[PDB]
Image (cartoon, rainbow, N blue to C red):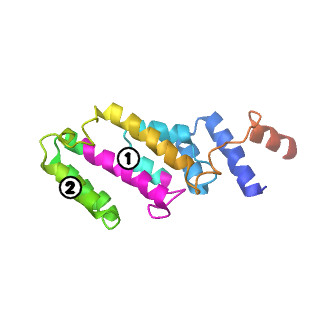
């Protein structure tokens, strides 16, 4: 019930058909009207953490609510574990201070336990993390958690469904009227 919002959905369908894919996602992000779950899934799967966070930023901030807090924490925790698994402690300690320290103030003992992982030979020595397989398996299990959190978050609840539109909607509307 907003022309600005109706136009965004019409434009998003034109861009998709035109295959201007980067523009599709920038419009979703910058407008905030539609969160593409299919896009987010692919991005999490390919470990493109910078784009995952930039995209999320168009819909939520890290401290907006408890769901938003856990979404960002889960992603940074995975980014961290992956640096540990590749035996890159300088990178893992860089992620801990720059990305995970923000949540230390909330659960302090959790942060201490996550920090302790840097000293283990293999982080699977920790009871909770013994079940972590490879990075492909880990990303899949976290994505299932991420998906639950987005669906249960009030800031995202009304932004997961794209309207049912006839193909070339914007093409057919401008052609008839611009005459």
The label shown at residue 49 is: 1
Q: Does the magenta segment cover residue 144?
A: no
Stretch in magenta: 56-82
Q: Secondary structure at mark 2?
A: helix
The answer for how far apart the CA atoms under marks 2 and 1 are is: 20 Å
Instruction: Choose between 47 and 76: the one closer to the eye.
Output: 76
The label shown at residue 115 is: 2
- Which residue is found at the position 17% from the left and 40% from the top? 125
Q: Secondary structure at mark 1?
A: helix
Asked if 157 appears above or below 131 in the picture, the reply is below
- Whole-percent x and y of residue 107? 32, 62
Quadrant (top left, top right, bottom left, bottom right) of the C terminus: top right
- Whole-percent x and y of residue 123? 19, 42
Quadrant (top left, top right, bottom left, bottom right) of the N terminus: bottom right
Asked if 32 appears above or below 147 in the picture, the reply is below
Please give left or right for residue 37 compared with residue 109 in the image.
Answer: right
- Whole-percent x and y of residue 160? 62, 45
Instruction: Choose between 62 and 149: the one closer to the eye.
Output: 149
Please say whether residue 54 is visible from this viewpoint.
yes
Asked if 83 appears above or below 102 in the picture, the reply is above
Of the numbered discs 2 and 1, the one sitting upstream in the chain is: 1
User: Which quarter of the figure has residue 4?
Assistant: bottom right
Depth-wise, is mark 2 or mark 1 nearer the camera? 2
- Which residue is found at the position 34% from the left and 51% from the top? 76
């Amino acid at each position: 019930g907003s022309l600005s919002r109706e136009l965004v959905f019409l434009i998003l369908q034109f861009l998709d058909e035109e295959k201007f894919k980067e523009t599709v996602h920038k419009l979703e992000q910058e407008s905030g009207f539609f969160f593409n779950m299919k896009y987010f899934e692919d991005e999490v799967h390919n470990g493109n953490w910078d784009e995952v966070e930039k995209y999320l930023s168009g819909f939520t901030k890290v401290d907006d609510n408890r769901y938003s807090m856990k979404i960002f924490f889960e992603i940074r925790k995975q980014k961290y574990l992956e640096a540990l698994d590749k035996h890159d402690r300088p990178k893992a300690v860089d992620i801990l201070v720059k990305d995970l320290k923000v949540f230390s103030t909330f659960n302090e003992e959790l942060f201490k336990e996550i920090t302790q992982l840097l000293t283990l030979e293999n982080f699977r020595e920790n009871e909770q993390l013994s079940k972590y397989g490879d990075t492909k398996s880990a990303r899949a299990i976290m994505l299932v958690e991420l998906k639950k959190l987005i669906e249960a978050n009030p800031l995202f609840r009304d932004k997961l469904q794209f309207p049912t539109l006839r193909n070339s909607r914007l093409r057919t509307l401008i052609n008839q009227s611009l005459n």
